Image 1 (tube, helix red, strand yellow):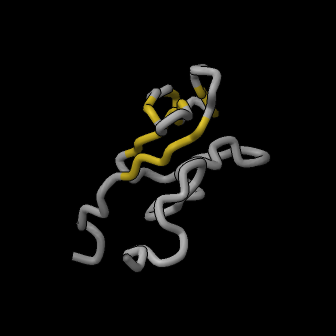
Image 2: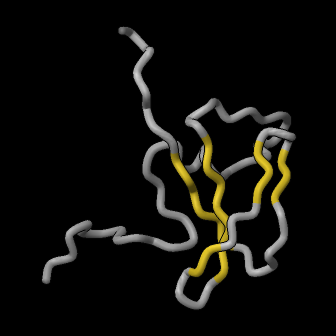
Length: 84
């Protein structure tokens, strides 16, 4: 009550056609290689922790998301139902 509530987790997709691994600031390290149709992308999933950075943000993944962002994919952008 007043916190103590699970605000879930988030996996924010980073598109990288290099299948390299992203190790930033010893907070986030992982390469989850997924099929984006014809694009290969990694994604960072976090237990909704706080995003630590130092001088200049080293993440820019979950701090762009942290709830519901659309990077290197664009789910629906305008009209999330898509009028069909």
